[PDB]
Image (cartoon, rainbow over all chains, first blue to last red; front, side, top):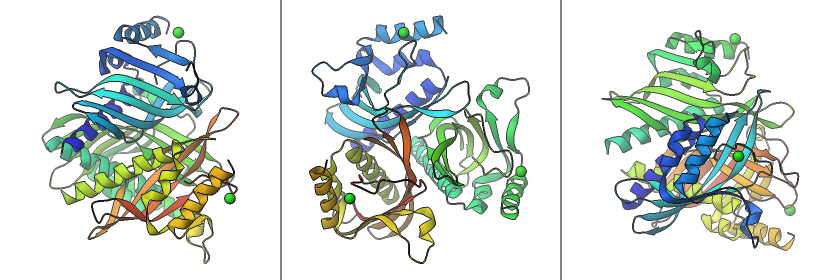
Length: 153
Length: 153
Length: 153
Ligand SMILES: [Cl-]
Ligand SMILES: [Cl-]
Ligand SMILES: [Cl-]
């Protein structure tokens, strides 16, 4: 029962996380994390390098918010499909999980292409009747990724 | 418990809806709607225009059935992946929800391409021990879409 | 309740099955099947031919293991997205189900492409407090598929 509850909570979180970004409700995105959080976007191969280079990196909620503010100030259509989560550990109301994802993007030419494929590797805080990310690492396969005014994965 | 029940009902509906179309069981498709229904397929940008042009439009079950009949009479391989649904409102046994989707298509050259990416915006009727669409709007990103003898999204 | 239990078991199985292959934990893959199993990969159109040609075929766990051994001995990045399962029959603790899937692949040029789209047609053994495949047929749309040292779908 407790397993089913955490599974559903995390899968609901991921569905709403994808729709928040795809709908361009970027202001909601930082609220899905705890204040003292970690969000990063790193290439699959870099997750073995001595110095894993993140191409997007936020080590506080303030940095998440800074990104949303900048994206609004210095103003494609995105679509996430996120797989069902695999829970990989439970220590009380802290739950680790992973879920595959693909972000599809449609630009001005009108063709929808695969923009970024990867998997989320997460630590969720399920305390206090809520579901928020303590840490999310987007471990990605696709080489080309936006480096200027990039919308979150 | 009631939330879990509606969530599961809608996610089961979407899984079976995608497989019905992909398997070419087109005769089942109109049965997934109530009689006095609305099905439409509209571009993301048109959902702000003064006159949102739908490229596929049915305002009764009779129109759904008319499409299936025509597709059979005047005879690609499709594959849907549908995200988990986000329930956006509940008024008794009427439930609104949204779910991301991508339809992949394989034509005679054998390459599988992204045909149509979007999100379903739905009103479900969960009354009377059943799950049927009152209305489904497929809000889509991908520019090119079939305009002759188009299979439903 | 029993329906919800089988649904969750199968959807959890599929999530972990995709991640096992994508993570290159190929040694886990044969363990997801019973010993006297059937795994095959067959083109959609061949599922009507008098002699349906399978392009990947294993009729025991020994054959599954033989493939993993060969892949290790004679050494792309893959990403599965698997749809929610539709349960198509239940005879005690043997359950038939189907689920759409797309395997995305990223090769040396760095572009992520659609490698293989299809649906799983499965017979699950849910006896003895466990979830294992009795048979899985991957019925696929995409023409080009690896024929040398192919990683499982
Ligand atoms: Cl920037
Ligand atoms: Cl027509
Ligand atoms: Cl081989």
